[PDB]
Length: 272
Length: 269
Ligand SMILES: [Zn+2]
Ligand SMILES: [Zn+2]
Ligand SMILES: [Zn+2]
Ligand SMILES: [Zn+2]
Image (cartoon, rainbow over all chains, first blue to last red):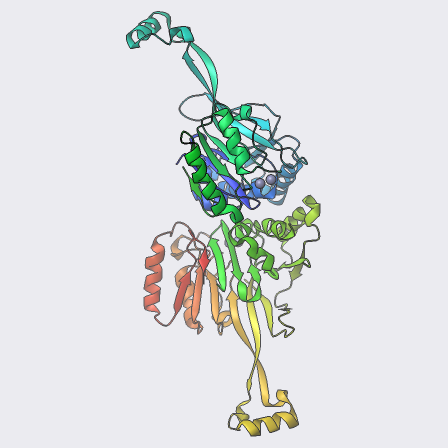
């Protein structure tokens, strides 16, 4: 599964994006739910430091440290620079359990700072944080996963199969293409409807939808519509608004046939 | 449900006992699973301070706070519980007065409010790790008065008092092992409900005697006169052998009700 996660507003939120071995947020229960799968984690990106987005980190590091043996690898954990709650909790984990001190590295990130990923299939993707409006208290980030790609220059897009192949054979691939950065994944974290520009072009939007501050579903769909996003996952949903949102979802699925709309049910583990 | 719990060895363990609004242990996920039921907690008793038994505590008080402080009891000397609760309060000023921790000495009783009856109390026993008994103080007619009729017994009670005609005895309503080896039959004997850890299904691969194997546990259940037992703290390795293994003992011991907490799902009873 490309994505396995769980999200219930105020209680716990965590999203495992398997393709890049990245865990976004770490609410309680992630290690219990994923088991030995936590050994496969290479990165943790935290949107912020509220307990429902970080309390599961201790279990992740504890299980990795006890179950990987001499083949354990340090877990890189990234969070919004200046977020004291993340720093206090990670310091407590290391202080309270010396055996875990070197099991993970905590890296504060500045907005816009890129982190290139190390996985199989090529060196071509990086994670990039953007500031979000949430508690107005501490710093929160949303994240994009970008993929460095190459596409044919406009002038060569009309050539047929044989013509483009002939040209590439003669002049090389780079000559007929230009590089561009595709947003392959966007996670909002807790925040108000993202600016249509922040989400435009993303192949998969994962946006909080706490209400029927945070964001209400209508403001989110409006944003998706303006940015022309085709695939969105709604999360950070509360249990009191289950059916109400569920109904508005089908309503939206009809009103927006070209857009795939999924949601993480606050009562069950999500998989895609 | 008198018991809603979840347990998976090394990952998370929490057992909510609704009759007394008591939560035993608080492994990660308890507030997420129980939701608003956490508002109902009257007490939390921790068997120890390993991450899989306490990481969910922050979540519980955070959700509760969002009304006297919740009382949290744990084994005296357990530094891990102290360090974690101190971190919660130091790092979250708003929760600083939301709960209180209380170290307990082995055998130290905590009488439960009740409706003012104080008929029930919790008592820890060593397994710093503690197991716990919930005791109910009951009364029964002294043997010498069993034959008196209604009028005769009331005349005696009037003249002598209720205490004179009855005798109080302490009944073990619930026993929770916490993490430990098979408990001495003496410790469990008499309990109406035993919830005992069952980390291994085969003692052969227990590099360290800090956990009980099912046969050993069943041995103690045998030696004592234990009615129903809920096996928990079960490891993932023995994920499927579970049924079988348990099916056999349900057979080799047809008088013993054997329930268990599947490491893959929340338990309800
Ligand atoms: Zn949140
Ligand atoms: Zn938040
Ligand atoms: Zn344990
Ligand atoms: Zn333990």
